[PDB]
């Protein structure tokens, strides 16, 4: 279709007061980045709840992807799902972000802001929802087709889901963390795609981004070894075109400079005693 441009935002959606806010709501920055990478058994139990709720919200919003829907409506459905299940939407009020999920159409790499933009036939849309409940976070995203998606765009989406799943399969105690981005990038590059560098996955727990970084490209200089009880996301963004990007005037929305489309998937993972468990169903 035509290159995207910003629509109009709807007003802030309320959250029932009884649902606890993360500490960072309304503040310039979050108190995150230096927390332990291995979680306690108590926190891991809590993170199974938050992950399940985030995965339900993402699935409910995904069911509404269809030509003619607005990205604001996806956000209303995600928001409603989270608050009906007792969870706060972690994006809402993180460094002022104004909505309860990120909706990233077509050439939007990440961090799209739900708004009056109407989806049309052929579009792809990433919906990224995080839930905060029991003092911990759960983060997941997926890219959904709207209507009759072109073969090159269908392939990019299915190969980005494959890359994410291949990477998840490598996770176990003792594995070098660098294998994740080796597996993602070696697979994506077979088809000539380019793996985004400047946005990464991350440890997650009682804080949204806890200071652990997970790269999605090949970077053998990272020495980090995976430990039982570590919790982190794998969330590669994969481009049909070049990596060069621009940020919109809202200071959030990241778009490819060449306007070629891009796809993402994300799960929150637990390193178990023997392998990996997807906490976001
Ligand atoms: C692609 O998006 C991921 C992403 O930017 N990661 C990079 C980390 C972003 C925050 C700062 N970082 C840290 O290491 C700091 C320790 C805190 C890098 C992000 O985690 C998404 O999955 C999440 O759903 C959206 C979060 C908002 C920022 C829109 C609310
Ligand atoms: Mn996310
Ligand atoms: Mn994330």
Image (cartoon, rainbow, N blue to C red):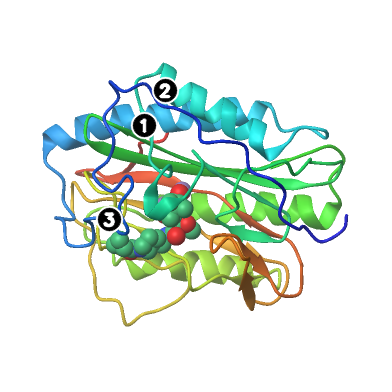
Counting other residues with Cα less than 10 Å from the Cα at mark 3, is it few (<14), some (14-19), or many (20 or more)? some
Which quarter of the figure is the C terminus placed in? top left
Residue at left offset 29%, top offset 55%: 203
Residue at left offset 11%, top offset 41%: 40
Is residue 233 found left or right of 41 in the rendered image? right
Question: Element type at marker 2?
Answer: helix
Q: Which residue is under mark 2?
A: 83
Is residue 169 found left or right of 236 in the rendered image? left
Q: Does the residue labelled 3 lie within 8 Å of ligand 1?
A: yes
Q: Which residue is under mark 3?
A: 30
Residue at left offset 73%, top offset 47%: 124
Q: Which residue is under mark 1?
A: 88
80 shown above or below 261 = above
Who is closer to the viewer here, 162 or 260? Answer: 260
Quick one: label 2 or label 3, which is nearer the N terminus? 3
Quick one: label 1 or label 3, which is nearer the N terminus? 3
Is residue 116 found left or right of 184 in the rendered image? right
């Amino acid at each position: 279709r035509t290159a995207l441009s910003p629509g109009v935002l709807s007003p802030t959606r309320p959250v029932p007061n009884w649902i606890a806010r993360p500490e960072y709501v309304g503040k310039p920055a979050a108190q995150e980045g230096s927390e332990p990478w291995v979680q306690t058994p108590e926190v891991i139990e809590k993170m199974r709840v938050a992950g399940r709720i985030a995965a339900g919200a993402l699935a409910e919003a995904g069911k509404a992807v269809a030509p003619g829907v607005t990205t604001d409506e996806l956000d209303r459905i995600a928001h409603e799902y989270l608050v009906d299940n007792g969870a706060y939407p972690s994006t809402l009020g993180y460094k002022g972000f104004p909505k309860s999920c990120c909706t990233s159409l077509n050439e939007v790499i990440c961090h799209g802001i739900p708004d009056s933009t109407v989806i049309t036939d052929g579009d792809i849309v990433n919906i990224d929802v995080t839930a905060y409940i029991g003092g911990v976070h759960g983060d997941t995203n997926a890219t959904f087709p709207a209507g009759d998606v072109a073969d090159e765009h269908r392939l990019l989406v299915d190969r980005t889901r494959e890359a994410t799943m291949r990477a998840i399969n490598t996770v176990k105690p003792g594995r070098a963390l660098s294998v994740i981005g080796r597996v993602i990038e070696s697979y994506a590059n077979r088809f000539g795609y380019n793996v985004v560098r400047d946005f990464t996955g991350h440890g997650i727990g009682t804080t949204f981004h806890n200071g652990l970084v997970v790269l999605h490209y090949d970077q053998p200089a990272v020495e980090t070894i995976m430990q039982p009880g570590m919790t982190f996301t794998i969330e590669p963004m994969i481009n049909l075109g070049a990596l060069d990007y621009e940020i919109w005037d809202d200071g959030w929305t990241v778009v490819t400079k060449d306007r070629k489309w891009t796809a993402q998937f994300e799960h929150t993972l637990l390193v178990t005693d023997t392998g990996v468990e997807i906490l976001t169903c």
